[PDB]
Image 1 (cartoon, protein in one colour):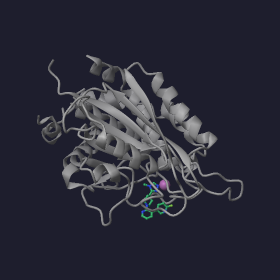
Image 2 (tube, helix red, strand yellow):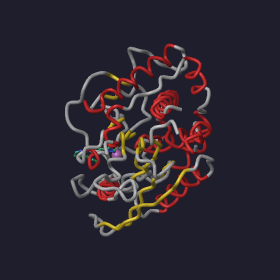
Image 3 (cartoon, rainbow, N blue to C red):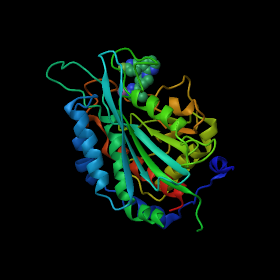
Image 4 (cartoon, protein in one colour):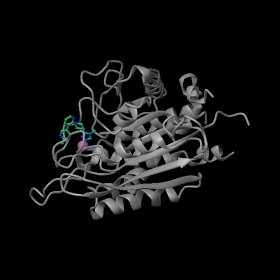
Length: 326
Ligand SMILES: Cn1cnnc1C1CCN(c2ncccc2-c2ccc(F)nc2)CC1
Ligand SMILES: [Co+2]
């Protein structure tokens, strides 16, 4: 069976003008700010009070949606620099037994830092905002998504991952990093899918991994990293332009735009690595450069850009709708 190949040929359903208008009007940046983003701007390294609440906040937010979301906690112990630690990835699937899933993901953990001048690192852009935008997407699209509960469709739904312990504890290295991802990846790699199949694993299931990281500084530039996924990048470029055209953005210029058609110099380590090395198509939505306030106490809410997150919300939402033909 050649269904793992279905993703290679899969095409989008290009929304038309008024559709795009209606998506734009559908997402409230401020609803998100207050309810999605704000609660997560807390110290939330693994095992911390913040961790448990962060995790509880996310499931609270999803559980309140009507689309038949299936939540699931990948909790595991692993050795670390600071000694043994419990990690818990949050997965959220619509239609889990569907062969194919588009997958959005980020990291809910934050990096550890000593309380330099009674200040606390909350990792705004890194990646509380990614988390919020995902949860906003989940909301903004509830009605539309609820239809994926019902002959004439590809066997494809949506999945959200929120990886834990992405961040390094001490020195970033193969073994002090990507704790959450490394584990789930290996688990998926060996979990048969669909249940009772020969050969094909849950990783065959991931049509595409869309990984949001370090998002919320103004004027981010995303490079196109992956050739094997460069066509979806192009859709993102198109959608950005389209909405700009219809004037459905706020404070945006084509000269100062987000998705640039250039490649990237080095190779960026993130949650996608364990997936990508197993031949998942990845779409790495991480800005190059990173925000100024990267791994600083300045990575705070004072320093996010309201308009930038909102615009991206609009872009990412259209992308996903088109990807799912909704
Ligand atoms: C993806 N992400 C989110 N927050 N920080 C990151 C990256 C992870 C990969 N990075 C590294 N790559 C190679 C060697 C070291 C690092 C690194 C990671 C964390 C840190 F504090 N300092 C360096 C840069 C920061
Ligand atoms: Co970081």
